[PDB]
Amino acid sequence: KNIDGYFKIYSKHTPINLVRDLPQGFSALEPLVDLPIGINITRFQTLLA
Amino acid sequence: FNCYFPLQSYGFQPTNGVGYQPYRVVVLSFELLHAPATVCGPKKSTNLV
């Protein structure tokens, strides 16, 4: 998210075991870094290898 | 005739007069607006009690 030009980055990492669909469980993310960029974002793209 | 190259080269020598000696001039422009964030002034701490 972007808050008054500050872009907040949240991340959480945990192992799982899944075949399909998605796991059902609770998680709590934490802020990684603060990026004082100050730009408007209206679209995004996903990067895959 | 009536045509000169706008740019001219400086003449710098150790024995040149004080007026012609090279002086490194750097201007720091500080602008106050609403677009965070940039460098802030020095922040000093004190002994903890």
Image (spheres, grey):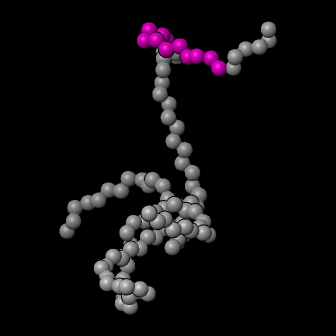
Residue lying at 39% horizontally and 66% vertically, measured from the top left: A33
Locate residue B36 relative to residue B7 in the image: left or right.
left
**Residue B8 against residue A6 in the figure, above or below:** above
Locate residue B45 relative to residue A36 in the image: left or right.
left
Q: Nearer the viewer, residue B41 or A37?
A: A37
| Magenta stretch secondary structure, dominant | loop
Give x and y (percent) for residue A46.
51, 68
Magenta stretch encompasses residue A23: no
**Residue B27 against residue A18 in the figure, above or below:** above
Residue lying at 62% horizontally and 17% vertically, measured from the top left: B8
Q: Quadrant of the C terminus of chain B?
A: bottom left
The boundaries of the magenta stretch are B7-17
Residue farthest right in this picture? B2
Q: Quadrant of the N terminus of chain B?
A: top right
Give x and y (percent) for residue B19.
52, 16
Tell me which corner region of the image, top left, top right, bottom left or bottom right, holds residue A32: bottom left
